[PDB]
Length: 214
Length: 226
Picture 1 (spheres, rainbow over the protein chains, first blue to last red):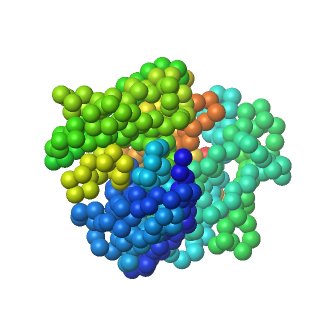
Picture 2 (picture 1 turned 180 degrees about the vertical axis):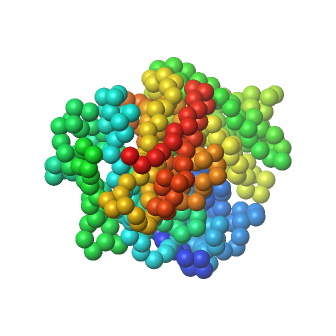
Picture 3 (picture 1 turned 135 degrees about the horizontal axis):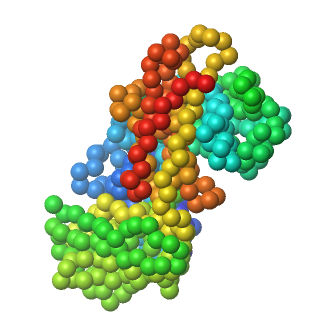
């Protein structure tokens, strides 16, 4: 089994930039390497095969090169429709093998997130479980750290996270974090806090409420 | 013109069976080898099976050997993938794909020319359940202010997907509907949020519309400050 390793895992660039993606193989694949483009919700789209042969209809800004073990996909001038994920594929031998993928994102200036915390509703409290939600709104870049604290106790293993794609109008991300407790545990403590670490923040931002009506 | 149409996906409990279909048109079907490729949610592409143009030779990934059977029917120009002993690890969107020819030469091992639209397979012991919808009420620590955030917690549904709109579609600016997360219980949960100006609170009503067609569930939850 031949394994492919793409680099980098993601890249932020502007329109007009020159982007270079590499694919490394554990063995020699002569020239049986293909490059694909994929946008969310749609199937992959072949761009290069034979490591340099452009598919019919693909713009000439997409160039592929390399042989043997090291390969390279190049976009000579990035265009708005080129922000997507790119995969290499090996066709030297069975099993067929894909690279992990390289996501090309839109670069923009740093944006610090607006943080909001939401206590559980009283309608959910009757079911026996409580969900505290924390929103990180319109930040960039994507790297962020959300830590939950209840009565200053750092929580672990009782939260889940979800991130949107880049917004179509300002290229920022948004993040939702949901802390899930039992109602008994929730009524047992007072102050619930959401601590957010981001490079747009000089100090971490913490939003908090305390259960009751405060 | 040249296309591959897929069918057969759905929700299935662990250990059961499913058969996928890929019908070809617009090109000579039995000159090409054919492949099945899947992609788990959030994951990358994984090749699962391939078959030669004549159906004499079949190739399988280690992850599906003894479990999946690929076959084809030349008269129908249709490709099949019989999947038995399904487990949650097999949850993915399945594609059929055609290897590209190189100047008339049909090789089974190449870049993949044409892809079907995909068909989704979900392997879970969960049963269809409508979502519980809870308000994410906007807050304050003074009386007036700037922009406020409110939202909708769509919790404990199965299967995907649910659709969320705000004020029957009249509110779109500042809306973020987050991808669902799969919980330990086997049920999904997502949240939709929107940022509004603080002057709107009290004057303007905010209703969150949640539709979950697999359970015929339709919920309108007004979100107001506590």
